[PDB]
Image (cartoon, coloured by chain):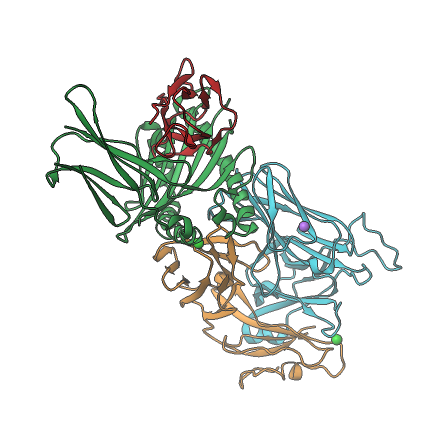
Chain colours: A cyan, B red, C green, D orange
């Protein structure tokens, strides 16, 4: 398939960034798109084959290098807040409508400064006794709050293994200060199990939030702990 | 592998008349492969001011070209088209039949 | 009248000479050119240059760079299938015709070393192969149903729409009529033989009909037909001869002419 | 050049949905549909260039070239079909024009609804029928999520829920969902 990196990146206005893209499908054509809410994918630059590249619809503020047949890198020379987006690399066998194969996507957030960057606080809320007696089911709730930017992945872990059945996580976070341009975020998730499974005191439940913040190379001059990429978790054990 | 030797046709733009300005054409066609050399000659010598079309493609996969020069025919002057191609061991000189 | 649009590609392995050339035509007129040396697609007719903005040329320059690369690889694969070394040629011709009677044709063909290799039939959606190497390629191409449908659509719809667009851009050239100037020359050749030549020049379009008739009827005798040749000024010339009441009959762009000898 | 497809569509689990796409392209070389799950990459679903309907499992894609129209038809809807569906047209210069996408929402078939609002030591509104809609918060210090569907696969059971929270002293589960039209029979323990 198509391998693109990084999955997430925070940048300060004026900083440089290179997104990597590689494919081992022997495709000739490669593409860089940005995806923004309410509109179709917009082509930034493309490369019809090794040895050539050309502008798409939105090339300003970007440049590309078709390094070889496999690789097509996208550069942001001086990051601007307007470049906050989800970037997708894609490839096709030829130029005449063969299906496009997409990379995983790269979520870039460009900020004037890093002073509002925060990891989430994570808390787990144990099932209601009233729900257990009324339904014979038990819903745990996880809340990830006060994070910024919105670069998180929430997962549930039962007895040290990730679960998907009985789980539902909000597809988008909510803004904790909707009137503020730099509002921090909150995300909720539920995990529902049977009353008996929750009643077992040996069953362990953990909600994990992977946050993508700052890197080692990012400068930090604030009094508070540097808001680096980190995992924040909250847990609960079963109760009789 | 099949190589096709060029057909070479030498003719004037308008019906020829001695002492009247005209154009001498050399139409080189039906050849394969594409590499070819064409010169127009006046009394055995290469004419310098010679125009030509770009290499052209026929539907039967062969190629064609048109070479031409402005000239004034006379009884004493002999005109020819000289062509070299892989199918020819030596350059072929094709004389204008004088219309 | 009948009009056509066609794009050709020529690939040469190990050339003396560009490795790749692509030329487009409308009727007998070159309209576009691209080669592996310039790496640019350019107009070959002023009516193409005046009607297509720089974005057309920029986009097709990128497309042709991609097609050039694919053509090189396909030719390498064909040489490997044939166990061929040295210099070999690969050619493609795609296009369509819009006939005067209203009917349309569409064609897509490949040649290896100047001989038919694969011929597409857009009506059956299949490739006709000349030999076992062409059959291997036909099997690989026919496995992609979407590509066959795409080629049929292109030939029948897109190609015809491009042709009508170019015909309008080039109407002052393509749709004009320059009638022929026709003459009959009589000559005693070998003793006792008389030859009659019906010669036409200065005409456009190149399509012309010329024949000889005897006492108002079709001949049984042999007519020698001269090729229709470019005169160099955008017009054409042709002839027809017979040996021996004879008359030459010429038809050009809806006009009939008779020259009685 | 323009691609038009509805912003959003909602249909019920087990039913059928038809997603229309109209294209106004400068020439035509094909019509594609791609599926894009939330937070994931778009993946190819279908391609049509001539007239007809092409079937691939539960999904079918139709094209009418004379109407400049296509649809993506999804049968026997499953919760996993909740995604965005992108329509893209290819023009005369083999360039793609991408539609803004249709977000498809699937309503679970709730067989035994038991609407209730529970307090967890955070308020949980759960087990209500798919027809019920959850309204956003009116107060800035009160946070309300949209309804989310969970699937307890081994129990062949699905349920809707929404979460409300606040650190304000006036906040109570009895008032948490006052901005929403909730079932009259909602259980408040
Ligand atoms: Cl606010
Ligand atoms: Cl067009
Ligand atoms: Na740029």
Q: Quadrant of ligand 1?
A: bottom right
Of residues C235 and D56, the one drawn nearer to the viewer in this rendering: C235
Q: Residue at x 78, y 52 (%)?
A: A15
- Can you say which quadrant of the picture contains the N terminus of chain A? top right
What residue occupies the far top of the structure in this picture? B89
- Looking at the rendered structure, the number of numbered marks drawn on it comes to 0
Q: Position of residue A125 (x, y in %)?
A: 68, 68
Side of C132 where A138 appears, left or right: right
Q: Residue at x 61, y 76 (%)?
A: A130
Of residues D66 and C106, the one drawn nearer to the viewer in this rendering: C106
Q: Answer yes or no: is residue A240 visible.
A: no
Q: Position of residue A51 (x, y in %)?
A: 60, 37
Q: Position of residue D40 (x, y in %)?
A: 57, 55
Of residues A31 and D42, the one drawn nearer to the viewer in this rendering: A31
Reply above or below: D163 against B23.
below
Side of A226 where C110 appears, left or right: left
Q: Position of residue B36 (x, y in %)?
A: 45, 23
């Amino acid at each position: 398939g198509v391998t693109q990196t990084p999955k997430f990146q925070v940048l300060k206005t004026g900083q440089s960034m290179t997104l990597q893209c590689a494919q081992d499908m022997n495709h000739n054509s490669m593409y860089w798109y940005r995806q923004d809410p309410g509109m179709g994918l917009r082509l930034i630059y493309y490369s019809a084959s090794e040895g050539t590249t050309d502008k798409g619809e939105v090339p300003n503020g970007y440049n590309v290098s078709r390094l070889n047949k496999r690789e097509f890198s996208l550069r942001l020379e001086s990051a601007a807040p307007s470049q906050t987006s989800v970037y997708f690399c894609a490839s096709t066998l030829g130029q005449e409508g063969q299906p496009q194969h997409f990379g995983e996507g790269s979520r870039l957030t460009v900020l004037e400064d890093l002073k509002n960057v925060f990891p989430p606080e994570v808390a787990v809320f144990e099932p209601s006794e009233a729900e257990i007696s009324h339904t014979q089911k038990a819903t745990l709730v996880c809340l990830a709050t006060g994070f910024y930017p919105d670069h998180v992945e929430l997962s549930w872990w039962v007895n040290g293994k990730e679960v998907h059945s009985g789980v539902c996580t909000d597809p988008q976070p909510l803004k904790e200060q909707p009137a503020l341009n730099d509002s921090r975020y909150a995300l909720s998730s539920r995990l529902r199990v049977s009353a008996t499974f929750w009643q077992n005191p040996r069953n362990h439940f953990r909600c994990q939030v992977q946050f993508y913040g700052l890197s080692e190379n990012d400068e930090w001059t604030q009094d508070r702990a540097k808001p680096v990429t980190q995992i924040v978790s909250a847990e609960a054990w079963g109760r009789a | 592998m099949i190589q096709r030797t060029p057909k070479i046709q030498v003719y004037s733009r308008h019906p020829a008349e001695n002492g009247k300005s005209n154009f001498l054409n050399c139409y080189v066609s039906g050849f394969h492969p594409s590499d070819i050399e064409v010169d127009l000659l006046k009394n055995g010598e290469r004419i310098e001011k010679v125009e030509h079309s770009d290499l052209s493609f026929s539907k039967d996969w062969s190629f064609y070209l048109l070479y031409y020069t402005e000239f004034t025919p006379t009884e004493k002057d002999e005109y020819a088209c000289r062509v070299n191609h892989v199918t020819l061991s030596q350059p072929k000189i094709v004389k204008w039949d004088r219309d | 009248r009948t009009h056509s649009l066609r794009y050709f590609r020529l690939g040469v392995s190990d050339p003396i000479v560009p490795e790749f050339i692509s030329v487009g035509y409308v009727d007998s007129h070159p309209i576009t050119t691209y080669d592996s040396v310039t790496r640019q697609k350019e107009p070959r007719a002023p009516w193409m240059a005046e009607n297509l903005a720089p974005d057309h040329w920029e986009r097709y320059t990128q497309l042709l760079r991609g097609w050039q690369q694919m053509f090189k690889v396909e030719l390498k694969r064909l040489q490997r299938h044939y166990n061929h070394s040295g210099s070999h040629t690969y050619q493609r011709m795609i296009g369509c015709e819009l006939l005067e009677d209203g009917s349309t044709t569409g064609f897509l063909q490949y040649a290896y070393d100047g001989q038919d290799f694969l011929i597409f039939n857009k009506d059956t959606l299949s490739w006709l192969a000349v030999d076992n190497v062409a059959h291997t390629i036909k099997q690989a191409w026919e496995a992609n149903q979407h590509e066959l449908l795409y080629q049929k659509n292109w030939l029948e719809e897109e190609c015809i729409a491009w042709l009508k667009r170019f015909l309008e851009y080039g109407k002052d050239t393509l749709q004009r009529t320059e009638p022929p100037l026709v003459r009959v020359n009589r000559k005693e050749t070998f003793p006792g033989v008389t030859a009659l030549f019906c010669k036409a020049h200065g005409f456009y379009p190149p399509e012309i009909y010329m024949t000889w008739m005897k006492n108002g009827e079709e001949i049984v005798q042999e007519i020698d037909y001269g090729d229709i040749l470019p005169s160099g000024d955008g017009t054409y010339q042709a002839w027809a001869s017979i040996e021996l009441l004879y008359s030459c009959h010429v038809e050009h762009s809806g006009v009939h002419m008779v020259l009685q000898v | 050049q323009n691609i038009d497809q509805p912003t959003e569509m909602t249909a019920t689990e087990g039913a059928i949905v038809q997603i229309n796409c109209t294209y106004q392209t400068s020439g035509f070389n094909g019509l594609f549909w791609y599926q894009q799950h939330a937070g994931e990459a778009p993946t190819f679903l279908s391609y049509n260039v001539l007239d007809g309907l092409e079937e691939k499992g539960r999904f079918s894609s139709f094209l009418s070239r004379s109407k400049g129209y296509s649809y993506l038809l999804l049968k026997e809807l499953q919760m996993k079909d909740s995604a965005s569906y992108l329509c893209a047209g290819m023009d005369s210069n083999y360039q793609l024009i991408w539609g803004a996408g249709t977000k498809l929402i699937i309503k679970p078939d709730i067989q035994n609804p038991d609407p209730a609002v529970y307090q967890l030591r955070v308020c949980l509104f759960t087990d209500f029928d798919s027809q019920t809609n959850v309204s956003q918060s009116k107060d800035s210090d009160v946070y309300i999520t949209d309804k989310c569907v969970l699937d307890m696969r081994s129990m062949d059971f699905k349920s809707n829920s929404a979460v409300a929270w606040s650190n304000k002293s006036d906040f109570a589960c009895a008032n948490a969902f006052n901005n929403s039209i909730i079932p009259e029979d909602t259980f408040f323990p």
